Image: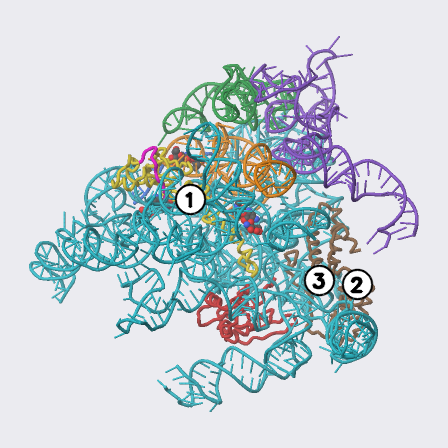
Chain colours: A brown, B yellow, C red, D purple, E green, F cyan, G orange, H blue
Amino acid sequence: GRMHSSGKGISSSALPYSRNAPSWFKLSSDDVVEQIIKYARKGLTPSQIGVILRDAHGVSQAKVVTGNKILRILKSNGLAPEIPEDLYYLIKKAVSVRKHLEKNRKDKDSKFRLILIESRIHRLARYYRTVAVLPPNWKYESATASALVA
Amino acid sequence: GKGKPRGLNSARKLRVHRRNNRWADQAYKARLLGTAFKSSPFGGSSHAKGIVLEKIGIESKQPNSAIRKCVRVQLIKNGKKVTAFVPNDGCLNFVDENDEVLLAGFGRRGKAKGDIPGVRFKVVKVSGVSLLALWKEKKEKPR
Amino acid sequence: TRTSVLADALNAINNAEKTGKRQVLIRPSSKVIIKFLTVMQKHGYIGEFEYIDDHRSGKIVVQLNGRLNKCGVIQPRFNVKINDIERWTDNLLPARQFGYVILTTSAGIMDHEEARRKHVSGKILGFVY
RNA sequence: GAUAAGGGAAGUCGGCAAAAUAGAUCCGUAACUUCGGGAUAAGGAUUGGCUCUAAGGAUCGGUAACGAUCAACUUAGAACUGGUACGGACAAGGGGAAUCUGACUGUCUAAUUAAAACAUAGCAUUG
RNA sequence: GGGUAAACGGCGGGAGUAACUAUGACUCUCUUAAGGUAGCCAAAUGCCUCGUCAUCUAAUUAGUGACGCGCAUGAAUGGAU
RNA sequence: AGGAUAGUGGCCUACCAUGGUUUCAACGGGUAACGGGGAAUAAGGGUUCGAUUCCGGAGAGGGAGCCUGAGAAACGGCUACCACAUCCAAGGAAGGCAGCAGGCGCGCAAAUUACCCAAUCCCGACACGGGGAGGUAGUGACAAUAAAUAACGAUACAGGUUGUAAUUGGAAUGAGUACAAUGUAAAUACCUUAACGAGGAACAAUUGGAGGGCAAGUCUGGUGCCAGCAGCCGCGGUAAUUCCAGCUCCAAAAGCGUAUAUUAAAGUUGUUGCAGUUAAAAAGCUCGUAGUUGAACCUUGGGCUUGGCUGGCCGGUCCUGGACCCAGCCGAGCCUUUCCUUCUGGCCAGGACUUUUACUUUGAAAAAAUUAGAGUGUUCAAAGCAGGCCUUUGCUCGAAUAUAUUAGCAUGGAAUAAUAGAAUAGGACGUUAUGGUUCUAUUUUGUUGGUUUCUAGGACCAUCGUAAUGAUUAAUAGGGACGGUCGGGGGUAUCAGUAUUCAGUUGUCAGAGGUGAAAUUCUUGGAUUUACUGAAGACUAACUACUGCGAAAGCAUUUACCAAGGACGUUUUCAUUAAUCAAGAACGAAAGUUAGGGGAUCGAAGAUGAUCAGAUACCGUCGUAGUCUUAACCAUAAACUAUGCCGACUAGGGAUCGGUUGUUGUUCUUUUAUUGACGCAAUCGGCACCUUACGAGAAAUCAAAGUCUUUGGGUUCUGGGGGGAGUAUGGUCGCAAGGCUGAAACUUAAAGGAAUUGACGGAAG
RNA sequence: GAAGCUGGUCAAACUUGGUCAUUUAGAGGAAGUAAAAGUCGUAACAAGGUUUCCGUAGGUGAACCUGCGGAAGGAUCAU
RNA sequence: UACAACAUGUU
Ligand SMILES: CN[C@@H]1[C@@H](O)[C@@H](O[C@@H]2[C@@H](O)[C@H](O[C@H]3O[C@H]([C@@H](C)O)[C@@H](O)[C@H](O)[C@H]3N)[C@@H](N)C[C@H]2N)OC[C@]1(C)O
Ligand SMILES: CN[C@@H]1[C@@H](O)[C@@H](O[C@@H]2[C@@H](O)[C@H](O[C@H]3O[C@H]([C@@H](C)O)[C@@H](O)[C@H](O)[C@H]3N)[C@@H](N)C[C@H]2N)OC[C@]1(C)O
Ligand SMILES: CN[C@@H]1[C@@H](O)[C@@H](O[C@@H]2[C@@H](O)[C@H](O[C@H]3O[C@H]([C@@H](C)O)[C@@H](O)[C@H](O)[C@H]3N)[C@@H](N)C[C@H]2N)OC[C@]1(C)O
């Protein structure tokens, strides 16, 4: 179920069985890669890039049309974010909640949700340090929180 | 399920959990606190001796009506005062104030017995001779 | 979350058996589940079972013949000496002439009589009778 | 103004008076508490002289982490030494356990009463 | 005629009553503006009085801790800490 | 580095560094703790005991220090001090029973100041001596073995062929005593034995019971809720099967009872294997570290040859086995892209290599005694390890055999569960690919001590040469993004609304108020009642429900802003990031606390009127805190669904809220679209509900409280008869009120749960 | 080569202060429990005659009463 | 409107 609530929703994208591109789709693998690079260079997280590709270029899964996943392609062409986008978005949400809270000191539900969000941030940062994606001594702190999202 | 861990490396939790909950059993708790050594009138002994201080009659509890003859006794080993029942018909006349009696438990390992409230001991011997012998005129009270 | 897929499979099999179902769907599947099901099939307790490929973990549909009383897992997978199998068969099995204690051994997954023939032991896996 | 054997408040309304303590370094420090204190609590050790050693700097000159020139007294350690002395004169808290009472610092009967009296912050009432 | 006590001030008697005795939770009656509440005490406030018990001492009209029908304790005439 | 020691070592010294242990429980405290071999109980798993016949350690009243000696920090050795204790002529001197015996003390609790080196064995200069070590006896109902207290006839009986009766005889004998020998170091005892040794065979069996559990009396007398019994339930009040006795009967018997501890019964400690809705027990609720636990996936199928065992066609049957065949099981070798370290000798014997573990198999080794167990007429048995035969100058089987194993050392397997690898390639193989350097070097000009690269081997540094060059799914786990929504979720401003109270203006006059009924109270100064305006604080009616949101507590007027959220939709993204969680944190109704501000209304306390026997209660009238808000505390509720959380599965139905997906005889825009509402089918998530009883339960009841003796998905917390008691104490938090943590003594036979029948109700029909 | 002497070293023992563990006296005070037929009321069990109970805060001879907010374990599964 | 209580122990 949901990690920080009682919800048990199952609404997820359902990947197709076929691992080959459809016969009606004809775009070069090099073309799809350069499209990925163009979208990243303008500035777009891999989730955003995948959404645009699927919506406007018939690119269902970039994996089946390039043989490799988007974030792996970005790392192979020097476009991997310094902070993984999961952690980046969690820190951004925490910054937004903190800035809301500094005015509304009597909003106790916001304080409770801040605790939950920061718990998720620390668990994810722990995971990333374990797989050496983040430096061994990387640490999220609220005082420098706005920097990494700026 | 079952509320207890089953992991194959959970022996510490299981053993410590059993150790904590064994304190809820009276016999284990008594033998590990050493309450017989520290608070039992006999100090853990099966029998004890003492000097008779006074004869007292104790009203039997409901639905019985009687006077159970007993003696107030001061123990020798620790100076404690206990009440002991003197069991048989007319055996109270065999015991007197200042006599030395041998006491035993009263059958229920520290509890009262029957309709006699607050009495947990019984007289076995007086002046070095058993009451069963005196009651049956098998011996004589020494002097 | 899911901590033993063998446990889910055997529970689903037993529950479908008790309701009179001729067939049970198992999800997900695994090598251990398939080996255990093979041991149960070789003794006739189950019929044909079929593996569906979903490119994720697999599903299994089993043909139940109604000859099975109980299948279950022994969890945790206790270590068993060669001569501690006696107590496990005494405690888990209806009698000394039918039923099986399934062991995973370095010689492979098998039942306890095969383990005695090969003089091998390992960790207990479950039972069937 | 001094000293005094043995005793050590038996003196006396009352330890009045006197004695005892005392500097500095190190150690150690209870109840209670308004958490700020109590506290130098209590209570221990050390301290001379002499001969040494180490540490703490400034200005010049180009891994200068160096060389040169100059300079104030603090601290720490060691050896040696004596009729065991040494804050050697001077200077310099006695301490503890409680009760009554006023919270505290402060103030008054010049010339017999300094206190528990007065004041005080805080609190309340009145126009 | 109404209000007002952090205004001045005030804040009770007499009989009976429990299966040893004793005591009196309980009852009756007289009466007040109200009948001393929370606390505290032989206290710098208690006469009787060197009260009674305990502790302190060889021995204590002293000290301290208790007790309380308190001659005559007691709440900003502030009570208890 | 030294000193010291027999020697290693912070063992000690000097100098230097700042280390060492710990929630996987250090450190500290307690032990009515010497450890083990072992003992009892014992389905299994367990629980409890072990001072004590053997092994190891420590001590000799308490400490410390030593001499001698191979060996002692010795105590039946010394020195000193402390404590005990002895003699004395008063100067002085002598001590160590936790060795044997014995005494005092202590206590519930334990034996002679005996005999002896004969045996076991030890010591010495030793064949000879010594040994309270040891052995022998005394005491000895610790425990254990065997085993008397009677046996048989005939008369009269009797029975239905002897099962049953009193009075009629003869034998049998060991308890006891004692010649004797034997036994022994000498004895004592046993064993053999002469003479004795039984009618009440008085040479006389007891201990507890006789309502139930639990075997055996309603027989007699006594007592009369007394005396007493009674583990428990109970008995006893003038017909007691229960007390005191008599008789009779029962159980076990040289033994039986009592007390205490402990084991089984106890699945009432539960890993196997308990219970937590209501009987005891789910933390108020979320976060969260340690701990425990964690989706799936990587050599699978096939063929040939071949060794051993079981039953059968060959039967070969003397339980023995035979080409081959029917089967089955367990081995071994090659081939399939083929894993097995690499090279040298040429299925052993050498160099250079080696990812770590858990797990399981097999071996060596593992004091006796004890346990199990084979043999064996100790007269049997407990026991012991003896013994048995042709009959003596002798012979002869034996003194087995298993159990030990957590840890360690060897050893096969490679499932299960982990661990590391090639991703900014710093990646693998080039053996016979080339070069540059450098090191170690055999063979050398062998006449002794020199050279440098062709040279042998490491080892670096490049170039190039091969390779299919090298990255598992993305889980109806999780996380993140994106889209349109949906909410009485939160916060801050803002807009309402009537009502209540209080007023100021208007108008009339006798009452108004309140109750089951009154009274206190207000009223001609006009109370109450009517209309208008106004001032205050609260609150958010009606809509409003088996409906919504939130972690819970909770959340309901309008609007705007702030950030947050579930669900849904997704062919977006990461890739195990997860579950539950000691310690540690956020929030937490009401009441309560502090300081300001407000204080309409209700209203603890208080005042007061009634009812009442009394009511310092219910009822009536006031009314202080409080109720509201701001900034801080407090942390508790029947904080309840009295039901932990995550995950999987198991039976039917109709509704409802949110999202999405297909679709009309309907209403609305427009009569027509990309309108809105409504209607009809599918799904995902919710709050719930209905039927049945699969299955569960003691039942009430439960779609979970099911999938639980056919007992095991992961994990946290709690309970162990009722009380004492959530008390005392220590700690800790709080301004306080109090919160959290949290015993014991002692007491007691039930307390309790669900349901049945009845009775009862100031309950209904 | 004896007594004796110097400097060390191990260090008994005593005195004072600290600390930990166990036991223990006490005026008085406040509880708990037990014990045929004593007193006062009647709080609970029926709508127990004011439904009961939980938390919190006052009050009161006593059971207990009252305020605020909860629960049904209600005397209502319902308009 | 008002309605308090019923000594001990059994067979
Ligand atoms: C005073 N009685 C105590 C009672 O308080 C309780 O003690 C527990 C004690 O068992 C707990 O401790 C226990 O549980 C911890 C666990 C938390 O890790 C274990 O580590 C520990 O070994 C275990 N003894 C301790 N943490 C708290 C006490 N109140 O249970 C034991 C007791 C003796 O009955
Ligand atoms: C054992 N024999 C039975 C015995 O059970 C006897 O008991 C009753 C008992 O049930 C009565 O009943 C009692 O039972 C319970 C409980 C103790 O059983 C008591 O708590 C309660 O006072 C009372 N109801 C009590 N008055 C005593 C005997 N008359 O009833 C008759 C009997 C034959 O003597
Ligand atoms: C039920 N509440 C009771 C209250 O009613 C009162 O009860 C007494 C009770 O204790 C008395 O009884 C008591 O005292 C008698 C004797 C010494 O008087 C004893 O024999 C008896 O065992 C004992 N329980 C009884 N005789 C009268 C009741 N009202 O006792 C106090 C109490 C416990 O609160």
Q: Can residue A18 be seen in this view?
A: yes
Q: Which of marks 3 and 1 is in front?
A: 1
Q: In this view, does F742 lie above or below F452?
A: above
Q: In this view, does F510 lie above or below F574?
A: above
Disc 1 is attached to a residue of which chain?
Answer: B
Q: Do the residues labelled 3 and 1 touch (CB within 8 Å)?
A: no
Q: Is residue B61 visible?
A: no
Q: Nearer the viewer, mark 2 or mark 1?
A: 1
Q: Earlier in the sequence, mark 3 or mark 2?
A: 2
Residue F545, percent from left and from top: 60, 52
Examine the image and state in which quarter residue F481 appears: bottom right
Examine the image and state in which quarter residue C2 appears: bottom right
Q: What residue type is labelled 1?
A: Gly
The answer to whether F657 appears left or right of F279 in the picture is right
What are the residue bounds of the magenta stretch? B95-108
Q: What residue type is labelled 3?
A: Val
Q: What residue type is labelled 2?
A: Leu
Q: Which mark is residue A44?
A: 2
Question: Which residue position is annotated with label 1?
Answer: B44
Q: Helix or strand or loop: what does disc 3 sit on? A: loop
Question: Which residue position is annotated with label 3?
Answer: A131
Q: Residue B79 carries which label?
A: none
Q: Is residue A77 magenta?
A: no
Examine the image and state in which quarter residue F24 appears: bottom right
Q: Which of F3 and A69 is in front in this view?
A: F3
Q: Nearer the viewer, mark 3 or mark 2?
A: 3
Q: Which of G41 and A92 is in front in this view?
A: A92
